[PDB]
């Protein structure tokens, strides 16, 4: 769930407050339309899709599902005790968190006008 995702970020990208990722580009946060303004936006685009895919599994709600995972000594691990749904979301979240750490941050891309720039 979002809390867990929020926590995967704080551990993967300590140097940056998680809210910097809450509303950025066209995909990070809400929205799922338009052209990803940059690599970091691409990370979120892939993330949004992943979630969408996970939604196909019955009763599976990526924002709310509580899954099992851990982050220590620089490693993020989705544990073996996750059912299909949990396993999927966790992986969605884990992959995004890793992508985030590797993606450059462009202050100009924070809080952009979705209605006008993501069509
Ligand atoms: O999408 C991301 O990458 C993200 C990253 C950090 C925090 N929040 C994020 N998203 C996000 C998306 C919808 C609603 C919320 C909210 F509930 F906090 F408002 C957060
Ligand atoms: Ca989104």
Image (tube, rainbow, N blue to C red):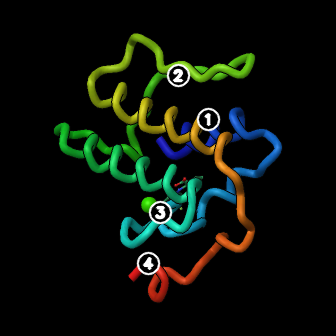
Q: CA distance from mark 3 to mark 2?
A: 24 Å
Q: Residues within 10 Å of mark 1 (few under 14, many from 20)?
A: many
Q: CA distance from mark 4 to mark 1?
A: 27 Å
Instruction: Name the spot of residue 65 as percent of width and height, x first.
Output: 38, 37
Reading the image, the residue beneath label 3 is: 27
Asked whether the beta carbons under mark 1 and mark 2 sit within 8 Å of each other, the answer is yes
First in sequence: mark 1 or mark 2? 1
Secondary structure beneath dot 2 equals strand
First in sequence: mark 1 or mark 3? 1
In this view, the residue in front, 37 or 51, is 37
Q: Which mark is residue 69?
A: 2
Reading the image, the residue beneath label 4 is: 118
Q: Which mark is residue 23?
A: none
First in sequence: mark 4 or mark 2? 2
Q: Is residue 116 above or below residue 80?
A: below
Secondary structure beneath dot 4 equals loop
Residue visible at 47% across and 41% down?
1
Cβ of mark 3 under 8 A from ligand 2: yes
Q: Which of the two marks, 4 or 2, is nearer to us in this view?
A: 4
Instruction: Name the spot of residue 69 as percent of width and height, x first.
Output: 52, 22
55 left or right of 27? left
Q: CA distance from mark 1 to mark 2?
A: 9 Å
In this view, the residue in front, 109 or 65, is 109
Instruction: Name the spot of residue 119 as percent of width and height, x first.
Output: 38, 83
11 left or right of 49? right
Q: Which of the two marks, 3 or 2, is nearer to us in this view?
A: 3
First in sequence: mark 4 or mark 1? 1
Q: CA distance from mark 1 to mark 3?
A: 18 Å
Residue visible at 66% across and 70% down?
110
Asked whether the beta carbons under mark 1 and mark 3 sit within 8 Å of each other, the answer is no
Q: Residue 83 falls in which quadrant of the image?
A: top left
């Amino acid at each position: 769930n979002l809390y867990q995702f929020k926590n995967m970020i704080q551990c993967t990208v300590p140097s940056r407050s998680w809210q910097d990722f809450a509303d950025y580009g066209c995909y990070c946060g809400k929205g799922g339309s338009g052209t990803p303004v940059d690599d970091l936006d691409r990370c979120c685009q892939v993330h949004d899709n992943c979630y969408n895919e996970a939604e196909n599994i019955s009763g599976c709600r990526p924002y709310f599902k509580t899954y099992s995972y851990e982050c220590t000594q620089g490693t993020l691990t989705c544990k073996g005790d996750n059912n299909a749904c949990a396993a999927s979301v966790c992986d969605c979240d884990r992959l995004a968190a890793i992508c985030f750490a590797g993606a450059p941050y462009n202050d100009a891309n924070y809080n952009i006008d979705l209605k006008a720039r993501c069509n």
